[PDB]
Image: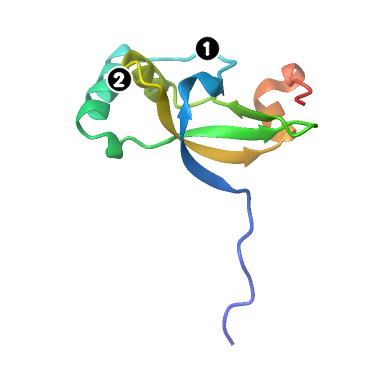
């Protein structure tokens, strides 16, 4: 008869997040022309610019941490526009997910 199964996975949700709340551990590789292209697009058609992906990690005592590894050109463009917030897809993630990026540097988040 009808379908047996469902899809289960981590929760993601789009939010306007303060640039300032994002932890950005790694240097950004940026094509200056691409940053400028994004600044122009944000000005004229911001809905066409997708939210940046952010790892939302809850620490051992429930603290919230928001890590940002990609989205570098968009982050740079919002910074150049002096924006307070940026559209971000907050993807619920774990310390083991974070380790994929930080390895032995992964902090014992509280």
Q: Is residue 14 left or right of residue 104?
A: left
Please tell me which residue is depicted at 63% across the width and 53% down the height of the picture.
Answer: 9
Horizontal and vertical percent position of residue 53: 50, 34
The first of marks 1 and 2 along the sequence is 1
Mark 2 lies on a secondary structure that is helix
Measured along the vertical axis of the image, is residue 2 above or below residue 24?
Answer: below
Q: Mark 2: few, some, or many residues within 10 Å (few <14, many ≥20)? A: some
Measured along the vertical axis of the image, is residue 10 above or below residue 108?
Answer: below
Q: Is residue 16 left or right of residue 64?
A: left
Horizontal and vertical percent position of residue 93: 65, 38
Name the quadrant containing residue 68.
top right
Q: Is residue 69 left or right of residue 31?
A: right
Q: Quadrant of the C terminus?
A: top right
Horizontal and vertical percent position of residue 62: 74, 34
Please tell me which residue is depicted at 54% across the width and 38% down the height of the picture.
Answer: 90
Mark 1 lies on a secondary structure that is loop
- Residue farthest to the left, as pictured: 44
Query: Which residue lies under the disc numbered 2?
Result: 34
Query: Which residue lies under the disc numbered 1?
Result: 27
Please tell me which residue is depicted at 54% across the width and 24% down the height of the picture.
Answer: 69
| Viewer-proximal residue among 63 and 54 | 63
Q: Quadrant of the N terminus?
A: bottom right
| Viewer-proximal residue among 84 and 11 | 84
| Viewer-proximal residue among 97 and 60 | 60
* Tag 1 near tag 2, CB within 8 Å: no
Q: Mark 1: few, some, or many residues within 10 Å (few <14, many ≥20)? A: few
Q: Is residue 33 left or right of residue 106?
A: left
């Amino acid at each position: 008869g009808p379908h047996m199964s469902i899809h289960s996975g981590r929760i993601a949700a789009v939010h306007n997040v303060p640039l300032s709340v994002l932890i950005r551990p790694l240097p950004s590789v940026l094509d200056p022309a691409k940053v400028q292209s994004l600044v122009d697009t944000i000005r004229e058609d911001p809905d066409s610019v997708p939210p940046i992906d952010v790892l939302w990690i809850k620490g051992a005592q429930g603290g919230d941490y928001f890590y940002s590894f990609g989205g570098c050109h968009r982050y740079a463009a919002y910074q150049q526009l002096q924006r307070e917030t940026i559209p971000a897809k907050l993807v619920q993630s774990t310390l083991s997910d974070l380790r994929v990026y930080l390895g032995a540097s992964t902090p014992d988040l509280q």
